[PDB]
Image (spheres, coloured by chain):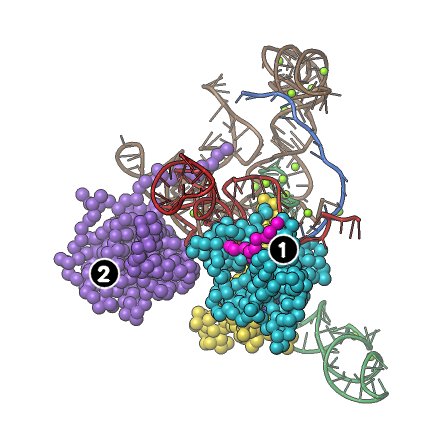
Chain colours: A cyan, B purple, C yellow, D blue, E red, F brown, G green
Amino acid sequence: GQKVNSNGLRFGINKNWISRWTANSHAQTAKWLIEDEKIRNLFFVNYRNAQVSNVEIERTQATVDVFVYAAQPAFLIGSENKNIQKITKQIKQIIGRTTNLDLTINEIGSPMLSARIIARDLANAIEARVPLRTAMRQSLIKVLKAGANGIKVLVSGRLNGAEIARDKMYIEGNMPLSTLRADIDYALEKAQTTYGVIGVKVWINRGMIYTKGLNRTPAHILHPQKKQPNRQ
Amino acid sequence: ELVSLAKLGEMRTHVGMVKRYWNPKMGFFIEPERKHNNDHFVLELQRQSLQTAYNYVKEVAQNNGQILFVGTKNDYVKKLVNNIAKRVDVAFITQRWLGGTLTNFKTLSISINKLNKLVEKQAENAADLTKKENLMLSREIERLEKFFGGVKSLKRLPNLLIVDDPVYEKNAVAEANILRIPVVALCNTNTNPELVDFIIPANNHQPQSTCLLMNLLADAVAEAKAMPTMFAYKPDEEIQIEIPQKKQITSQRLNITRNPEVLTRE
Amino acid sequence: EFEERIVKLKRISKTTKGGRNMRFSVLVVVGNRKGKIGYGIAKALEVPNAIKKAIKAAHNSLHTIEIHKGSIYHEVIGRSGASRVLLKPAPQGTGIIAGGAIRAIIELAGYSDIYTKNLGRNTPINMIHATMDGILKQLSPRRVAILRNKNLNEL
RNA sequence: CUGCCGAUAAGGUCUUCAAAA
RNA sequence: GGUGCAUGGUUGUCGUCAGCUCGUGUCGUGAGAUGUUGGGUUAAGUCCCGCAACGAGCGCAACCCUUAUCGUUAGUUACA
RNA sequence: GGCGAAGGCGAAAACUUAGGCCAUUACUGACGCUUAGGCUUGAAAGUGUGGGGAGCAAAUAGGAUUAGAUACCCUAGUAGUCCACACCGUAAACGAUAGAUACUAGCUGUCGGGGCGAUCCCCUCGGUAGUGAAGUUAACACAUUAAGUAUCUCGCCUGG
RNA sequence: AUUGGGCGUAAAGCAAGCGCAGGCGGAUUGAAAAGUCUGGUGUUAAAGGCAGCUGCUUAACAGUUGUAUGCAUUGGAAAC
Ligand SMILES: [Mg+2]
Ligand SMILES: [Mg+2]
Ligand SMILES: [Mg+2]
Ligand SMILES: [Mg+2]
Ligand SMILES: [Mg+2]
Ligand SMILES: [Mg+2]
Ligand SMILES: [Mg+2]
Ligand SMILES: [Mg+2]
Ligand SMILES: [Mg+2]
Ligand SMILES: [Mg+2]
Ligand SMILES: [Mg+2]
Ligand SMILES: [Mg+2]
Ligand SMILES: [Mg+2]
Ligand SMILES: [Mg+2]
Ligand SMILES: [Mg+2]
Ligand SMILES: [Mg+2]
Ligand SMILES: [Mg+2]
Ligand SMILES: [Mg+2]
Ligand SMILES: [Mg+2]
Ligand SMILES: [Mg+2]
């Protein structure tokens, strides 16, 4: 049957919001809401070879702050800070010159156990004509070796160019979806294949959060260092 | 010598089961029949078979083999195997023989490893256990001890099996045979001789014959391990044993009325 | 170097309360080409896992094979169900004149020259059963000497 | 505790594959 | 604009019913069986026993919110 | 449970009559097994002639039920079911397993003859059943009364 | 399906019996020698068959030498 979004079921209890701002009026609540979606989509659609895991947005009456986590930030940084200037101009055109931006790339730790880049890698493999069975298994084994709990991958679509759509799942371990205390990270991606669209869904279990609180604490960014800059 | 022929006769180790219950393939050990109604045995064959089994188990225990004792029959036998376990550090399975205790040893190895880890955790103790959780962990310890308390010691498949009754332990003897592991048993006229290797013609229903023979195999192990013997190489006064409670003792198989025709008709 | 070759890949299925549970079954023959050969049939939801389990089962049950001058010593008929496979000694040069599941077994065992004919069914499992049964009932010309008290095959 | 209780147009998907990692 | 009978995504339904499977092992030439069926207890494949089965995953349950009593902090724009 | 080769045989008696089991220091001395063709028997229904007919009931009439009911239900009801003599020669006529011969673990019943002598129970020789390993089978299953290891002879089968 | 198949549940044991001709058939001794085995001789036309060689540029082909099968007669063997 149908299931409630795993990310959406855990918001406001154990998971913080990706955008944290309070608008002035119901007219300014819509502009500030579509614009941040454009920024997030920009980061995700293009600049994909970087493995951007999550982009957070922080806005005040007039000051915009962006916290961008990536696995390989060299591509964003570019050759002696070139590509970086380009993206700043991109961000300024979307929000406006009248405001103040404080974009912040922040390098990420433990990149494997994140459902976003795994789905992106999965989608790239399917688009690259890689056999589906082999592609998921290599991603599954590497993620488990990274030192996490069970992972559930559902890859539904016109499998292998077939005319009848199927779906292949591969769970390997305890994925307690009905439990609220668990840390389940979820992401979904659309692999654009020449024979249509492939939907990949990745459920990852990253332990149990036994410390009550609406997070305010990082998630799989702590193990190695996490810095770099571009801020003020 | 090992034992005395009069002692075997007085312990009733030369008396099998009612002639109605016998496998025709066990005719070698049952001397020509007569007016006895419990199928008697040849005492010379008894001693010869016992000596051969004694020699082999001694060789294994001297060369540091791992022998496993499996008796999951009458209560007496259970207490007997526990007493033998106290005397010699041989692994034992007194409760029901789990399916694949030997052939699928990996899974039961995981279970006994879990048992040991839980035991040391409880021994190391913590105030986090409180009352409810402490009782749950204690009860878990009891269950994995009741069914793995004698199997915890060994870490690899045993090199020898001692079975009280091959008929009752058909699962155990089958596992030993498929894995090609020696198994000795006290056949009691109703057993297939092919499955067992070192056959020891004997009784199985008398709480005296069983104990005498079971201690005798244990006695070989104890001498190989260099601890003093209990019944073997011993005179009359020290072999004497008592008949458990609860004229002559009656080794008759009855209760036939509890075998009607399989429900049929239409 | 225990080589392995699939001899059949059937597509078995059971029926549940709506739909059909489909599992692949593989019949692998493993042989070192020196006298050791086994067979293993396994079922799994996917071909790779089925092949792994079948090879594991096949390697668990390995029988010992004796060769005489590269061929089979005496003509023998292996029976298994309704499948009867005839094996006949061959002179050095004919090659393996076998075909199908029997041919796979003979090559994987080590035998070279061998005359075969399948006189019964064409089900791969029973033909392999019959072939292995025929090869396992074979009598060496040294065992009969110990038995019949002859002179190590001497006339 | 035995009333009564009849029918259901044709042809059709769906397993691609283990070579292997 | 056509094709939800090419799909992705989302949803109704059996049904918040208590189920659906896998790994290893064993039986069967084989589809397959075992566990998951027996006896008790529940809303529950919830649990305990028995048991050629031993374990595991998803579901079930609890962790989440709210209402029902009380303690503590705070006393305005409530109370007074 | 018994008998007969099968169909079949169950109130009592008389007459005639068939086969069978057990023990044989008796006798003949291979005279034995199978059987194309041939002959005999062969459930029930059906036929021909003459009797018989209480009950029951194909066909038939009516009342119900039913969308319809030439059927299931009910009330009547002829042939028939019965006997004697003549035919018909078919049945799931089945143990769905032709007959004969020798061998191959065992256990539990039951029937008959013989040996002992209260029965009961023990042994021997046979008939009829259940369970059961090697063995056979595609599996179910058969398993000393074989569908097992073999021989002889007859009958029969060759996709729907 | 002589070599080389089957008839309980898949095609196939006649409904059963009395049974002539036919097929098969206990043990031992003697003779004969119809089957059975073996030796000698005759014959089974030539081409073709298989082996070797030669000749055509090698081959296809042609020639060349070898190569059985059965029947009859005669001389022995005596296990069935
Ligand atoms: Mg249904
Ligand atoms: Mg009605
Ligand atoms: Mg649809
Ligand atoms: Mg069970
Ligand atoms: Mg259970
Ligand atoms: Mg009649
Ligand atoms: Mg009318
Ligand atoms: Mg009437
Ligand atoms: Mg009439
Ligand atoms: Mg007929
Ligand atoms: Mg039976
Ligand atoms: Mg035709
Ligand atoms: Mg046929
Ligand atoms: Mg038929
Ligand atoms: Mg008949
Ligand atoms: Mg018939
Ligand atoms: Mg006759
Ligand atoms: Mg005659
Ligand atoms: Mg000629
Ligand atoms: Mg020519």
Q: Looking at the rendered structure, which numbered label has been put on residue B69?
A: none
Q: Quadrant of residue F53?
A: top right
Vertical placement of F139 versus G59: above or below?
above
- What stretch of residues is rendered in magenta? A15-25
Q: Are marks 1 and 2 on the same chain?
A: no
Q: Secondary structure at mark 2?
A: helix
Vertical placement of A218 versus C142: above or below?
above
Q: Looking at the rendered structure, which numbered label has been put on residue A32?
A: 1
Q: Residue at x 63, y 77 (%)?
A: A79
Q: Would residue B136 be visible to someone looking at this image?
A: yes
Is A22 positioned to the left or the right of B75 in the image?
A: right
Q: Residue at x 46, y 71 (%)?
A: C143
Residue C132: image location, x then y, percent: 54, 64
Ligand 17 image position (quadrant): top right
Residue F112: image location, x then y, percent: 40, 34
Is E22 positioned to the left or the right of F36 in the image?
A: left
Q: Is residue A103 magenta?
A: no
> In the image as oriented, which residue stretches furthest toward the left?
B237
* Magenta segment main secondary structure: loop
Q: Which residue is tagged 2?
A: B87
Vertical placement of C57 versus A179: above or below?
below
- Choose between A129 and B237: the one closer to the eye: A129
Q: Amino acid at mark 2?
A: Arg
- Give the letter of the chain under mark 1: A
Q: Residue at x 34, y 56 (%)?
A: B148
- Count of all numbered marks drawn on residues in the image: 2
